[PDB]
């Protein structure tokens, strides 16, 4: 039972890391879009 | 105690799934904004 | 062992809350970019 719990915890932590990676990927792309909007606005103004 | 731990684990996994859903929703909207920026830039150029 | 598991669970839940905060931050910024795109498109049209 202890080993089952330990395995379950490792699984959850692995999923958490996957989620963290996805968040990092979204942040990077979101930063590119912010930059793109700034450039387009500067042209429009 | 085993049952309490099992319940706690299910709760955590449920929250993880909720988080995964939110990430998926953000990715979809972010994709729309990327497309919108591409169309606006093409008009500006 | 029970205490180790309890500590591990608290750690995981704390990370989950951190993730939730980051998601909330991304959503807010994404909302600003959606608004910016709407304003730029209205000028272009």
Image (spheres, coloured by chain):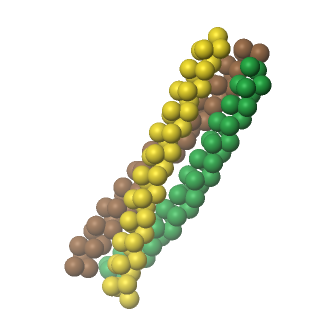
Chain colours: A green, B yellow, C brown
Can residue C20 be seen by looking at this rendering? no
Q: Residue at x 55, y 27 (%)?
A: B10
Q: Which residue is drawn at 44% across and 54% down?
A: B26
Q: In which quarter of the image is residue A43?
A: bottom left
Judge whether C43 appears above or below A7 on screen. Answer: below
In this orientation, which residue lies closer to the viewer: A37 or A29? A29
Q: Quadrant of residue B42?
A: bottom left
- Where does the N terminus of chain B fall, quadrant-wise? top right
Q: Quadrant of residue C44?
A: bottom left
Q: Which residue is drawn at 53% across and 57% down?
A: A27
Judge whether A35 appears above or below C32 on screen. Answer: below
In this orientation, which residue lies closer to the viewer: B36 or C1? C1
What count of labels does the image hold? 0
Left or right of C35: which side holds C9?
right
Can residue C13 be seen by looking at this rendering? yes
Where's residue C32, x and y in %?
A: 36, 58
Which residue extends farthest bottom? Answer: B45
Where's residue C31, x and y in %?
A: 36, 55
Where's residue C38, x and y in %?
A: 28, 67
Left or right of C40: which side holds B14?
right
In this orientation, which residue lies closer to the viewer: B28 or C28? B28
Q: Which residue is drawn at 65% across and 45% down?
A: A17
Judge whether B26 appears above or below B1 on screen. Answer: below
- Where does the C terminus of chain B fall, quadrant-wise? bottom left
Judge whether B9 appears above or below A14 on screen. Answer: above
Where's residue A18, x and y in %?
A: 63, 48
Left or right of B40: which side holds A18?
right
């Amino acid at each position: 039972r202890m080993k089952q719990i330990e395995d379950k915890i490792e699984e959850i932590e692995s999923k958490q890391k996957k989620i963290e990676n996805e968040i990092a990927r979204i942040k990077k792309l979101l930063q590119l879009t912010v930059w793109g909007i700034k450039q387009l606005q500067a042209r429009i103004l």
